[PDB]
Length: 277
Image 1: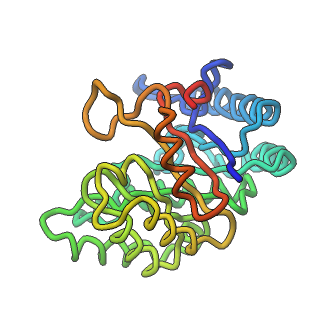
Image 2: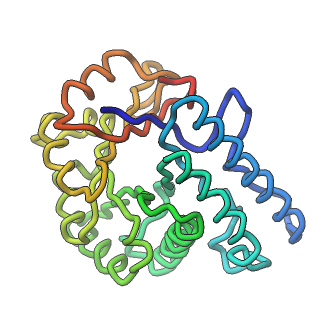
C-alpha cells in the first residue's frame, strides 16, 4: 500500500540525469556527448530501481541539455526517439512510474510575456519527452509560481496560458508550496484546468491553510484517474524553511502513513536521494 521513489540522481551508482554545460559556444558534439551520458545513466538508474524495489523516478530537466531553447543545434526528437522508446519500454516492463519537476523559475502565470514564453517552451519539452518515453501514467509536477502583488489575477493568468496546451495537460499535476499556494488554493486551479493535485507534505506543514494533512489528502486523492501521488520530505534542522534534510525522519513517515485515505505513490525528496529514506 506504498510505492517509493527518488528524484534525478543516484548516489551509490554515482549516476545522474541532470548534467548541464557552461562553456561558451557549445558545439553540437559537446551537447550530444552530455545527452548520451544522461541517457545512459537513466537506463542505469531504471535497472537499479528494478533490483532495489523503487517504482518511482523523476527525470532531471537537463536530460537533454537546453532542449527547450531555440538555439538547440539539432533535432533531439528525431535523434533520440528510438532510445527514449527503448528506455520507456524498460520502465513499463519494470512497472515504473516516471515524472518531471520543472524548477520554480518556470512560471506560466507570469506578468512578463518573455518569461511566459520560456516557461511554456520548457513545459512543451518535458511533456514531449514524456510522450517519447511512453510514460502514460507519467506526471508533470508544477508549482503555481509567483503572486506579484495580486494573487487572484496571477492564478487566472496561470490557467489562461496553460489550457491552450493539450500535450502538457496530458501529464500536468499541480503542487502546493511553502510560500504562496496551499492545497486548497492549488485545488482551485487544478479543478479549473482538469488536472490532479500533488500534496507536498513538508510544503503543507510550512503552509497549511485551514486543512490538516489528513483532509488535504482526502481532498486531493479523488483528483487522480490512476494512483494518487505524494511528495515527501523533511525540514533540514540547520537550514532555511523548505530546505530538505539528508534523510527523511521516522516521524515524518509516521504522519504520512497515518494520514493516507488509501494506497499512494510517494516521491521521496531527501538530499541523500535513494539513501535518504
